[PDB]
Amino acid sequence: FNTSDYRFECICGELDQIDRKPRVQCLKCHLWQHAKCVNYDEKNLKIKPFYCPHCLVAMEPVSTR
Ligand SMILES: [Zn+2]
Ligand SMILES: [Zn+2]
């Protein structure tokens, strides 16, 4: 019974390590994406909250009745 499939990786499918490309660990859905793939940076990763683009859209209302 499929409720939530546990596939979590950055949408480019290259790496996930701040050595090469900075990465945000989207706490809201345990999704490991890149900062420079979600329009974010590692400098404020130290400070501010960080998510994958789908969680932004999901917090926003959907066009339906
Ligand atoms: Zn990426
Ligand atoms: Zn997310």
Image (cartoon, rainbow, N blue to C red):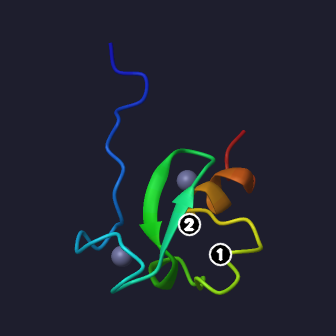
Quarter location, residue 16? bottom left
Identify the residue at image location x=36%, y=49%. Answer: 8
Q: Are marks 2 and 1 in contact (CB under 8 Å)?
A: no
Identify the residue position indicated by label 2 in the image: 53
Return the disc, 2 or 1, that comes first in the chain's sequence: 1
Label 1 SS: loop
Q: Is mark 2 within 8 Å of ligand 2?
A: no
Quarter location, residue 64? top right
Inter-mark Cα distance, 2 to 1: 15 Å
Identify the residue at image location x=48%, y=85%. Answer: 36
Horizontal and vertical percent position of residue 31: 46, 52
Identify the residue at image location x=64%, y=51%. Answer: 58
The amino acid type, in three-letter code, at marker 2 is: Pro
Left or right: 45, with 25 as reference point: right
Identify the residue position indicated by label 1 in the image: 45
The amino acid type, in three-letter code, at marker 1 is: Leu
Residue at the limit of the structure toward the left, as seen here: 14
Label 2 SS: helix
Identify the residue at image location x=65%, y=75%. Answer: 45
Horizontal and vertical percent position of residue 59: 72, 52
Horizontal and vertical percent position of residue 46: 69, 75
Left or right: 11, with 26 as reference point: left
- Residue 7, label in figure: none
Q: Is mark 1 within 8 Å of ligand 1?
A: no
Is 32 placed above or below 11 here? above
Quadrant in which the C terminus is drawn: top right
Ligand 1 shows up in which quadrant of the image?
Answer: bottom left
The front one of 17 and 59 is 17
Closer mark to the observer between disc 2 and disc 1:
1
Horizontal and vertical percent position of residue 23: 47, 72
Within 10 Å of the Cα at label 2, are there few (<14), some (14-19), or many (20+) other Cα atoms?
A: few
Is 6 placed above or below 24 here? above
